[PDB]
C-alpha cells in the first residue's frame, strides 16, 4: 500500500518468515471466564499413564479415593482469618498436603518445610510490622549512636501500604487492604456480622398468636439475628 | 535497526500512527531487561531440576507481582458484594454539598 | 408501540405473594441445637458449625450465596423467576393440634450470574463475547421495572422556590463556614 | 450464531423457572420499544420537585418501562409569587404591591390551622416588608399560633 | 494470641516507646499471612514437580523464597540452592562488543 | 456555539469544564495544578468588603490550586457551583472551595489513577471512574466509598448519572457500557454493539434514550427499556 | 513486485496475535475455601436425580476437576457432569 519505504528494508528471511504467521499456533485458552473457572474448581490427580501407574503403585501411594479425602481435609482447615492466630504445625501440614494434592504431587510433604514456612511468615510479617512501626514514630534512641505508647490503626496499615508498597504479595490481600480496610464513621465495625441491617432499627416480634403459626419474612431475619 | 521498524509495524498494526522517536527505544530497552531477567531465572530453574516449561516457571514467578492480573472480575465481584451489603446512609435534604466532620477535612492542620 | 399491558413483579414481597399456594424450593428445619437442610418430597443434619453461621448471613440478607449455583442445577430443584423459596421450620416454637413456618425469598446477584456462566463454561466451551451477549439478553428479559422518569431540577427554577432550601457557604466575621457532618 | 443464542436463552428461562406463557410475555415485553412519556422533563404544570426527605434513593416501587402510561408547602408557593412580582418595577408594579398583602394573610390563616411551626416560619419570613404599609395589624397577628388563637 | 507476641518481639519498649496493634490490623495481617502461605506453597509445588519428583521437599520452598522474595533463611538446604554462575557473556557477545568498541574508536 | 480557546498550554492541559452561569472555568494541567479562570474578566479574589492588604501580589484574574501530586485527568463542578471536584493520577479525588481557593477534603478509595469524576444531578453524591475496572460511588461527607461498581472487563473511562440521580452509567474500554442500580450496586443494563473504547456518555433529559461516543468516531443511541 | 510482497507482509502482521504462556488468575484463599465449604454442604444435602450417573468422586459430590498426574502444565482439563 503506502509502506513501501518501511516494509522493504526488512531482510528477505524476515519477510519470508512474516508472510507465514497465522492464528492457530497454540493450544491455549483465552476465555477469562473459563480461566477463572479452572482456577476456582478443586481438581484431583488421576492416573492413565502405565509407567506412572507402576511408579505410584510401587511407592505404596494410594488410589484417588485418598487424595480426594486429602483435598477435603486440606480445605476443611480453620484458616487463619477465622482463628485470629498464626497457624500451627498440623494446620500447616494439612493445608500444604491439600495444596500438593491440588497441584498433582501424590507423595509426602516433608516435616522441615513446615518450619521453613513458619520462619517465612515470621520474617514477612516482621518486615511489614516494622515498616509500619517506624513511620508513626521517630525512635530517637534507635537509628543513632548518641513519646508514649501508640497503637497502629488500619488507616496506618493502609498509609504505609503505599509509601512502601513493595512489601506485599500483591494478591487478594493487598487488594482488600486497599479496598475495604478503611471504614467511614457510620461503618458499625464492632458488630456480629448482621446488625447493620435496616430492620434492626425498627421491636422484636412475639410468637404463636395463630392456629397455623405461619409467620412473615421480617420475623425470620429477627430469628436469624439471635444466632 | 530491524526492531525499530518492526516496532513501527507493530505500532501501526494496532492503529498507532503518531508517536515520538524514543518510544520504540523504550520498548526495546524494556524487552531486553524482561528477557534477560526471565532467562537468568530460567537458568536457575534449569540448574535446579533449557526447555519451554522452564521458561513457563520463570515467567510465572514474576507474573504474580508486576503486570496486569488475569480474570479479576470474579474477585472484584466478590469484593463489591462485600461492600454492597451495607445500605446507603441518610443524606442531607437541604440540596447542597455537605462536608465531613472538621477533623476529617484538610483545614485544622498546621505548619 | 406496545401490544398488551404487562404485569411483572421485581420485588421480594410481591413475588412471594404471587408465589404462595405453590410448592417450595428448599426445606430448612430449626430443631433443638441442630439443623437440617432437606429437599421437598440421606439428607444431612448439621452441628452448629461455621458454614451455617455464614449461610445464615445470606438469609437475613435475602440473596442466594454465589457458591451454590451449579449444584442447584445438579439437584433438580424448582426455581421461581430466578429466585428460590426457602421454607424455614422453627420446631422450638411449635404448636399442638406443626412448627412455626417462615417463607422467605432469596434474590440473584451479579455473582450468581457469573458463577452460573462459569459453570456453563464446563461443557459448553464458549468465548467471552457469547457470555457478554447472553448476559445482555438475560439482563434485558429479566430486569424490567425501571425508574426512568425525571423530576424538576431545583437549581434552574431557583426564582420559584423557597430561599433556604439550598445550602451555600456564607461569610462570617473574618472567616467563612461550610456545613459539616 | 444468534438462533443458537436464542435457544440458549429459552433453555435458560426454562431451567431458571419461567412458565412458557411467562417467558413468551417477557420476550414480547423485551422486544417492544419504550413508549413516550408526555411529561418527559417534567413540565412545570404537571411535574413536581423531588422530595427532600433525607433518605437515599431507591429504584423500587416502580413498574416496567414497557407498559403504556406514566404537601407542597405554603412558603415556597408564596415565594414563587413574591419573586415574580418582585422582579418588576414596570407599569404593573403597584397593583401587585396592592394585591400581595391579603394572599399572604389568607395563606397564614389557612396554615395556622394545619401546621403551627411552618406558620411561624411563614409569618416571620415575610414580616418586615409592609409593616409601614399595614400598621400594627401584623403586631396584632403576633399572638395567633393555634386554632383557638384565631 | 500469637500475633501479639510477634508485634511484641518487633515492638519492644527499648527505652523509646512500645508500639501495640489493634484488632482490625490483626484481621488484615492474618489475611495477608493466610494468602502468603498458599502463594508460597503453590509455586513450591510447581518447582517440586519441575524436579520430576512427588515429595515436597524444603529445597523447593527455600529456592522459591530466595529467588523471588529474598527472605534468605539460613541453611536448611541452602548449599544446593546457592547456584554460582558468573554470568559472563558468550564469545559472540564479546566479539560484538569488540566491533562496537572498534567503531567507537574509529569514529574519532 | 461560543468557543473558548486556551493559548499558551504546551500540550499539558487535560480535560476542562465550565461552571453553570459560565463564570468559572477549570482546567487540569499535567504538572498538578488546577487553573481557575474567571470567564467574565472579574476579580476572582472574593474580597469581602473588609479588604485587609496584599495588592502587592499579581492577580491576572486567574487562581491556581496546588493540592495534587499527580496529573489531573478529570474535574467536575457542583450544580451549586461553589465547590470543585478534581480527580488525579495520585490516587485521591480532592475537593476545592471556589470562594476561598483552598482544598477541603481528600477522598481516598482508589489504588489506580482517577479518570472521570462526576457529581449527582442534585449534588448529593459523586461517582468516579478509574483504571482498576471498577466505578465507585461516594458521598461528599464520607471519606471512603459507598458502592463499588464491578463487572467490566477493562477499565472504566466515563461515568454519568441518570438525571434523577438514581442510576449510574459507566462506559469502559472493552467496547461496552453498563447501567448500575445505585442502591443494590448490581448492573441493570449492559449495552453491546460498539467497536472501540467508549469515551463519553450522556443520557437525554427525557431519560428513555442513552447516547454515547467511542474512539471510533461513531455515536450511537439505545433505549434503556429494550436495551438494543 | 514489491506491492504483493508488501501486502502479504501486512497480511502476516495483521494475523499474528500473542497469548501469554503463564497467567496467574487473581483470586483468594478465603473465597475459594468458603465457596468449597458452602458447595460441600449444599451438595451433601440434596440428591442428584440422574439419568445414568451423578458427578463427583469420594467425598466431593460436586463438579470436580480431572487433572492428570502428569501434564500438570496443561491449560485445560475435563470436569465431572451428570451423564444420562
Image (cartoon, rainbow, N blue to C red):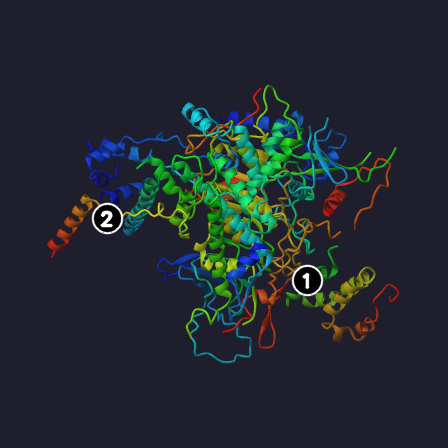
Q: Identify the secondary structure beneath mark 1.
A: loop
Identify the disc placed on residue E32.
none
Q: How many marks?
A: 2
Q: Position of residue B14 (x, y in %)?
A: 35, 41
Q: Position of residue F36 (x, y in %)?
A: 46, 64
* CA distance for labels 2 and 1: 82 Å
Instruction: Return the residue nearer the eye: D60 or G79.
Output: G79
Q: Is residue F89 visible?
A: no
Q: Residues within 10 Å of mark 1 (few under 14, many from 20)?
A: some
Tell me which corner region of the image, top left, top right, bottom left or bottom right, holds residue D40.
Answer: top right
Instruction: Return the residue nearer the eye: C156 or E6.
Output: E6
Query: Where does label 1 land, which residue?
Result: C162
Image height check: is F214 above or below G3? below
Tell me which corner region of the image, top left, top right, bottom left or bottom right, holds residue C9.
Answer: top right
Query: Where does label 2 land, which residue?
Result: E88
Image height check: is F120 above or below G47? below
Tell me which corner region of the image, top left, top right, bottom left or bottom right, holds residue C52.
Answer: top right
Parent chain of label 1:
C
Q: Is residue D126 left or right of residue F172?
A: right
Q: Position of residue A109 (x, y in %)?
A: 48, 39
Q: Residues within 10 Å of mark 2 (few under 14, many from 20)?
A: few
Amino acid at each position: 500500500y503506502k509502506k513501501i519505504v518501511m516494509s522493504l528494508p526488512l531482510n528477505d528471511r524476515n519477510r519470508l518468515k512474516m508472510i507465514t504467521k497465522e492464528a492457530g499456533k497454540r493450544g491455549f485458552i483465552f476465555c477469562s471466564v473459563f480461566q477463572a473457572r479452572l482456577n476456582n474448581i478443586p481438581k484431583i490427580p488421576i492416573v492413565t499413564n502405565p509407567e506412572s501407574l507402576k511408579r505410584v503403585k510401587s511407592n505404596n501411594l494410594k488410589t484417588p479415593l485418598e487424595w480426594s479425602q486429602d483435598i477435603m481435609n486440606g480445605f476443611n482447615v480453620p484458616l487463619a482469618s477465622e482463628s485470629h492466630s498464626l497457624p500451627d504445625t498440623d494446620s500447616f501440614y494439612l493445608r500444604m498436603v491439600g495444596i500438593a494434592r491440588e497441584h498433582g504431587l501424590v507423595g509426602t510433604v516433608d516435616a522441615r518445610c513446615v518450619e521453613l514456612i513458619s520462619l517465612a511468615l515470621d520474617q514477612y510479617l516482621k518486615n511489614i510490622i516494622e515498616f509500619t512501626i517506624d513511620t508513626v514514630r521517630y525512635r530517637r534512641k534507635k537509628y543513632s549512636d548518641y513519646s508514649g505508647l501508640y497503637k497502629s490503626v488500619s488507616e496506618m496499615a493502609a498509609d504505609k501500604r503505599d509509601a512502601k508498597i513493595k512489601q506485599l504479595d500483591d494478591d487478594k490481600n493487598e487488594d482488600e487492604c486497599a479496598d475495604e480496610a478503611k471504614s467511614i464513621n457510620n461503618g458499625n465495625n464492632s458488630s456480629k456480622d448482621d446488625i447493620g441491617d435496616i430492620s434492626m432499627s425498627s421491636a422484636v416480634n412475639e410468637e404463636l398468636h395463630e392456629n397455623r403459626t405461619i409467620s412473615l419474612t421480617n420475623e425470620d431475619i429477627y430469628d436469624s439475628l439471635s444466632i | 535497526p530491524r526492531d525499530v521498524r518492526l516496532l513501527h509495524l507493530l505500532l501501526a498494526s494496532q492503529s498507532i500512527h503518531q508517536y515520538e522517536d524514543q518510544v520504540p527505544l523504550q520498548l526495546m530497552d524494556f524487552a531486553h531487561r524482561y528477557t534477560q531477567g526471565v532467562l537468568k531465572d530460567a537458568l536457575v530453574y534449569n540448574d535446579y531440576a533449557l526447555g519451554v516449561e522452564d521458561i513457563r516457571l520463570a515467567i510465572a514467578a514474576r507474573t504474580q507481582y508486576q503486570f496486569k492480573p488475569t480474570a479479576p472480575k470474579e474477585l472484584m465481584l466478590q469484593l463489591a458484594a462485600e461492600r454492597n451489603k451495607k445500605a446507603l446512609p441518610q443524606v442531607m435534604g437541604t440540596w447542597g454539598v455537605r462536608l465531613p466532620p472538621e477533623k476529617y477535612c484538610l483545614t485544622a492542620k498546621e505548619w | 408501540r406496545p401490544k398488551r399491558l404487562y404485569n411483572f413483579v421485581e420485588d421480594a414481597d410481591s413475588i412471594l405473594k404471587k408465589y404462595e399456594q405453590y410448592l417450595h424450593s428448599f426445606e430448612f428445619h430449626i430443631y433443638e441445637n441442630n439443623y437440617k437442610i432437606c429437599a421437598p418430597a440421606g439428607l444431612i443434619l448439621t452441628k452448629n458449625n461455621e458454614t451455617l453461621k455464614e449461610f445464615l448471613e445470606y438469609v437475613a440478607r435475602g440473596r442466594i450465596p454465589d457458591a451454590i449455583m451449579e449444584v442447584l442445577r445438579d439437584c433438580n430443584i424448582q426455581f421461581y423467576e430466578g429466585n428460590l423459596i426457602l421454607q424455614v421450620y422453627d420446631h422450638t416454637n411449635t404448636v399442638d393440634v406443626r412448627p412455626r413456618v417462615y417463607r422467605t425469598l432469596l434474590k440473584p446477584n451479579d455473582l450468581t450470574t457469573y458463577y452460573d456462566m462459569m459453570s456453563y463454561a464446563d461443557n459448553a466451551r464458549f468465548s467471552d463475547s457469547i457470555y457478554q451477549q447472553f448476559e445482555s439478553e438475560i439482563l434485558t428479559l429479566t430486569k424490567r421495572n425501571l425508574s426512568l422518569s425525571v423530576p424538576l431540577n431545583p437549581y434552574e427554577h431557583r426564582d420559584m422556590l423557597e430561599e433556604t432550601a439550598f445550602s451555600e457557604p456564607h461569610w462570617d466575621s473574618e472567616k467563612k463556614s461550610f456545613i459539616h457532618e | 450464531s444468534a438462533s443458537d443464542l436464542n435457544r440458549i436463552v429459552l433453555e435458560y428461562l426454562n431451567k431458571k423457572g419461567y412458565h412458557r406463557t411467562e417467558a413468551m410475555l417477557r420476550a414480547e415485553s423485551g422486544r417492544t420499544l419504550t413508549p413516550q412519556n408526555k411529561q418527559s422533563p417534567a413540565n412545570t404544570k404537571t411535574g413536581k420537585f423531588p422530595e427532600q426527605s433525607s433518605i437515599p434513593p431507591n429504584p423500587g416501587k416502580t413498574a416496567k418501562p414497557i407498559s403504556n402510561p406514566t404537601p407542597e408547602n405554603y412558603i415556597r408557593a408564596y415565594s414563587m409569587l413574591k419573586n415574580w412580582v418582585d422582579s418588576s418595577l414596570e407599569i404593573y408594579k403597584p397593583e401587585l404591591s396592592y394585591i400581595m398583602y391579603p394572599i399572604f394573610i389568607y395563606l397564614f390563616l389557612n396554615l395556622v390551622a394545619k401546621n403551627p411551626v411552618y406558620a411561624r416560619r411563614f409569618f416571620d419570613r415575610f414580616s418586615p416588608d409592609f409593616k409601614d404599609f399595614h400598621g400594627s395589624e401584623i403586631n396584632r397577628l403576633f399572638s395567633v399560633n393555634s386554632i383557638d388563637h384565631i | 494470641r500469637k500475633l501479639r507476641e510477634l508485634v511484641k518481639t518487633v515492638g519492644i519498649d527499648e527505652g523509646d516507646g512500645e508500639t501495640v496493634i489493634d484488632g482490625d490490623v490483626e484481621e488484615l495481617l492474618l489475611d495477608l499471612a493466610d494468602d502468603f502461605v498458599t502463594n508460597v506453597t503453590a509455586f513450591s509445588c510447581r518447582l517440586a514437580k519441575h524436579r520430576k519428583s512427588d515429595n515436597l521437599e524444603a529445597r523447593d520452598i527455600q529456592l522459591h523464597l530466595e529467588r523471588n522474595w529474598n527472605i534468605r533463611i539460613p541453611g536448611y538446604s541452602a548449599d544446593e540452592i546457592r547456584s554460582t554462575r558468573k554470568w559472563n557473556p558468550s564469545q559472540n557477545y564479546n566479539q560484538k562488543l569488540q566491533s562496537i568498541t572498534s567503531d567507537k574508536v574509529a569514529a574519532a | 456555539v461560543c468557543m473558548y480557546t486556551f493559548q499558551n498550554t504546551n500540550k499539558d492541559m487535560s480535560c476542562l469544564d465550565f461552571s453553570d452561569d459560565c463564570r468559572i472555568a477549570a482546567a487540569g494541567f499535567q504538572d498538578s495544578y488546577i487553573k481557575i479562570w474567571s470567564l467574565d474578566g472579574s476579580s476572582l479574589n472574593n474580597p469581602n468588603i473588609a479588604l485587609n492588604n496584599n495588592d502587592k501580589d499579581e492577580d491576572p484574574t486567574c487562581k491556581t490550586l496546588v493540592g495534587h501530586s499527580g496529573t489531573v485527568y478529570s474535574t467536575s463542578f457542583s450544580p451549586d457551583n461553589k465547590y470543585l471536584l478534581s480527580g488525579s493520577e495520585d490516587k485521591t479525588v480532592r475537593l476545592w472551595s471556589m470562594d476561598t481557593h483552598t482544598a477541603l477534603v481528600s477522598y481516598k478509595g482508589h489504588n489506580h489513577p482517577v479518570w472521570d469524576v462526576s457529581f449527582s444531578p442534585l449534588g448529593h453524591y459523586f461517582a468516579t471512574a478509574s483504571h482498576d475496572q471498577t466505578a465507585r460511588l461516594w458521598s461528599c461527607d464520607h471519606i471512603y466509598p459507598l458502592r463499588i461498581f464491578a463487572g467490566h472487563l477493562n477499565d472504566v473511562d466515563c461515568v454519568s448519572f441518570h438525571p434523577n440521580g438514581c442510576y449510574v452509567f459507566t462506559g469502559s474500554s472493552d467496547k461496552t457500557c453498563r447501567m448500575w442500580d445505585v442502591s443494590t450496586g448490581d448492573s441493570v443494563r449492559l449495552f453491546l454493539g460498539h467497536t472501540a473504547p467508549v469515551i463519553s456518555i450522556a443520557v437525554c433529559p427525557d431519560g428513555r434514550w442513552l447516547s454515547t461516543g467511542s474512539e471510533d468516531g461513531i455515536i450511537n443511541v439505545w433505549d434503556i427499556g429494550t436495551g438494543k | 513486485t514489491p506491492e504483493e510482497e508488501t501486502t502479504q507482509v501486512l497480511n502476516g502482521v495483521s494475523r499474528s496475535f500473542p497469548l501469554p504462556l503463564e497467567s496467574t488468575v487473581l483470586s483468594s484463599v478465603r473465597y475459594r475455601t468458603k465457596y468449597f465449604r458452602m458447595r460441600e454442604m449444599f451438595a451433601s444435602s440434596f440428591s442428584v436425580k440422574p439419568g445414568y450417573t451423578s458427578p463427583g468422586y469420594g467425598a466431593i459430590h460436586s463438579r470436580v476437576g480431572c487433572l492428570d498426574l502428569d501434564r500438570t502444565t496443561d491449560y485445560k482439563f475435563r470436569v465431572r457432569t451428570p451423564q444420562p
